[PDB]
Image (tube, rainbow, N blue to C red; front, side, top):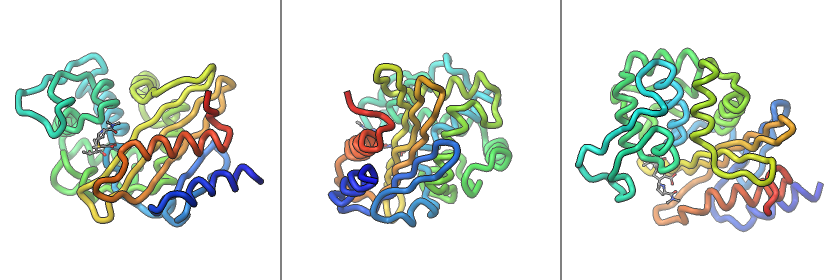
Length: 243
Ligand SMILES: *C(=O)[C@H]([C@@H](C)O)[C@@]1(C)CC(S[C@@H]2CN[C@H](C(=O)N(C)C)C2)=C(C(=O)O)N1
């Protein structure tokens, strides 16, 4: 089609290895300059916040109303120097809040919950507040896309109210009837550094298009490029047209 061409021509602009995967419940579609990336496992980085919230709510280690208090030790960013709910930390990608959550879960529950749902290679090593940021946990774009697809459908192995709560922590914007949910990620502590823009689009007519951008990142890159590249693709596909 000409849709594909317009989509690929977008990537013909970008000088970084990238793949963009879509999943509608039937077919995987892959776009970008390095298609092989879709099958390659990278660290989830801050995309793991989705499964961290799920496991934590499912196992009574937090609620979506509980306030995670700033403990006075300044954080990497100044925007992180306050109190957060898990939903608020989800949009601000507040890492220390989600590290506290991982420490509340602990290594034994975290491991067995990840085996139970089959998330990536299901490997955490020895530091329970670090495995998604530096490894050994890794996951393919195809796996991320099918994961967030089931989330949107309520079909993950978690209580339906728990998926509903983490789902709405991901809500970004709606255009007329169509809803966009998304989570970004930048694993800087690894070589190569990996960028993520995972999420989905919920039509009003029930249908769901999950998506996963995965690209290589350089120190200094445009922190906004992951989201603006994904919205351009989704518009070129006709899944989430610009207004
Ligand atoms: C997660 O992947 C990553 C590490 C520290 O866990 C994290 C939280 C840092 C960044 S960069 C920074 C956080 N949010 C900012 C942003 O996107 N905007 C629009 C201001 C930049 C990210 C990231 O996803 O970019 N995640």
